[PDB]
Length: 61
Image 1: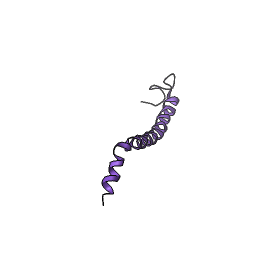
Image 2: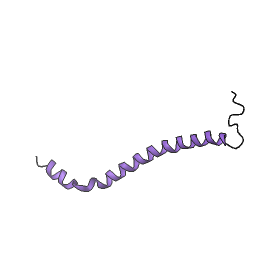
Image 3: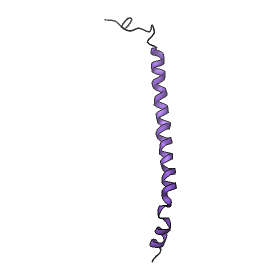
Image 4: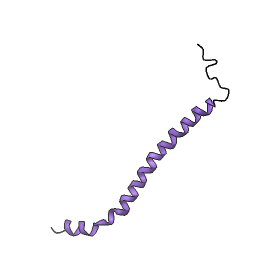
């Protein structure tokens, strides 16, 4: 066999293959962190479901 022939680098865009892989790696990292932040916002917006009921029932002493 040999590594100088089996699908060499004629038009398989190998260099771009590795560069693209790195792009998805980072995009995913910032993506997981960005998505988490959004979840915190939602819960923060829906947290107003029974707030007044939490203080009235939590302050009944």
